[PDB]
Image (cartoon, rainbow over all chains, first blue to last red; front, side):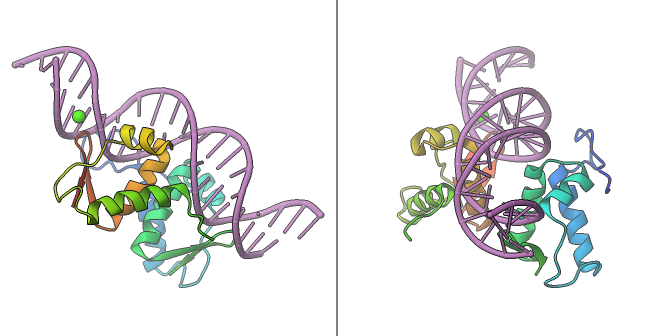
Length: 81
Length: 70
DNA sequence: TAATATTTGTACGAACAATTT
DNA sequence: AAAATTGTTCGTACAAATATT
Ligand SMILES: [Ca+2]
């Protein structure tokens, strides 16, 4: 269960939840916590662990895929590029 | 097959506009409300299409302003 | 000058399809 | 044959920024 800094975008440090989830996952990648063609946790596991909606998980992942450090296979899972 | 998902088709149409020069750079495309009434699809679908095209460098957006040809 | 309306942004939920396990 | 997992598509409610009255 990873924690959100969530509250008060009104001043400075606040990021949207999808951006925070994004930072975590990406930090997992280059820190080598998961290597290329290794599977990351399912959208459902991510939902529970970050305490956010599937929509928010899919946005975070959708972005990282488009950056090209993840790739997805429908029905298979999502993997470090 | 010739089938493409709805967001891909909205994507195609908008793109064609751009490269046929029906909207030039720094020029505005229809709003999301207009795009959805014209394609008869959801705001979500419209936002998905536009998001992809921003991500590929074809468009930029300004919250509260609108969306524009890059 | 200040309210209001308009428009894009983030974030929750729902149901079903398509593909893989 | 079923179950699990990602894909598409609809919906609702506010927040935040800009553009209009
Ligand atoms: Ca406006």
